[PDB]
Image (cartoon, rainbow, N blue to C red; front, side, top):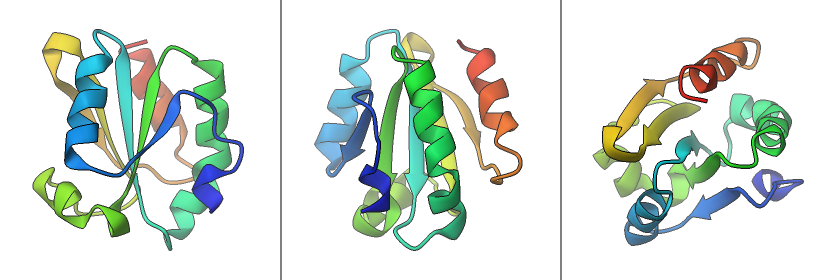
Length: 117
């Protein structure tokens, strides 16, 4: 599957609600970037290499990949309405970013990271 190709060790597939919370809790005070994507999302597929490169460049950021099509109830509960979409979480602060971005507007994701390192 395209979302598995060249994905580094800080990029994890989320397949259940409990696993999602455990990942957020176990992250401690680390920045967590949650990548909501779809199996047939062209933009998602197109930006994946850039996302993988970003993860390699930031080994201490945790990237959680959430396939909307395989976790629909979870994504709906989280108010995710369009794909690609991102939530950032960090420790006690909980959710600290919530946004979409284009392939060409990938710099918005980099700017979001820089707001939280």
